[PDB]
Length: 49
Length: 49
Image (cartoon, rainbow over the protein chains, first blue to last red):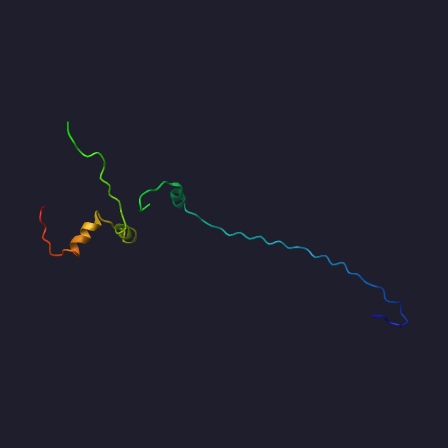
């Protein structure tokens, strides 16, 4: 605000603001059975397989 | 010299045994003959031929 008072005149002002980035790390764990893995690779032809 | 079959007989769990094999844990040889005698001819005495 431009004043006409007895103090020194108003000077323009800059403020240096330093914004950073916080990182957040998430892991979801999954178990798969070893007999469930083994018949994914296996060859199958009968309608029960 | 003799004359027999050339291949194995094939038994496979098809669409009606496969429901009772999964769900009940019991299957049966030739479901189609058991169903065609209990409900289709319930009074048919066991004859040989």
